Length: 180
Ligand code: HEM
Image (cartoon, rainbow, N blue to C red):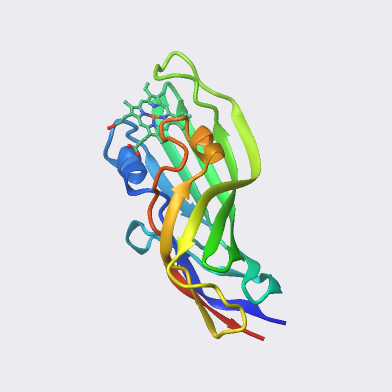
């Protein structure tokens, strides 16, 4: 039995999006919950107790504590951009990983304040593919989470279609310690 007992995934999705929300035309806010930390905009998520499943030295899943709530485009008393990301998971396959999230997000209806989307629940969405700097090996004492990230087709759609499929996101960072 091996489990991720310490460390953090450090990832703020995409700096241009955080800037878009906080200082750009969205004029909104970012709020972290459930244990996530800011860590300079490279949001830090801790591994969840019992959150590690290992199927092979190079394959497994680590579930993380934390959530991110994006708000933008305040129209009347509603926010037209209202996206919550939770249940963050990292699924490892050697030098590759996937970043999986649950999303609760208003549908994008167009670039007007004359219309607002209803909340769409998107569970278990693969948001990004990760190219890890080093191969994940759950038989070792640590896993380096550093790597580059590509947005998936479904992630692009979940974020209003403004990004193209395969677009680069923030690189992943951090590390986990694995023990018995
Ligand atoms: C659910 C609703 C919405 C979502 C998910 C969404 C998402 C996004 C995303 C991901 C970007 C790219 C930001 C970046 O990284 O550069 C963007 C940019 C932009 N969006 Fe939104 N958006 C929404 C609603 C709206 C609305 C209602 C408007 C206008 C009425 C709008 C106008 C814009 C503009 C002008 C940009 C370009 C900003 C820039 O380049 O400075 N969006 N949006």
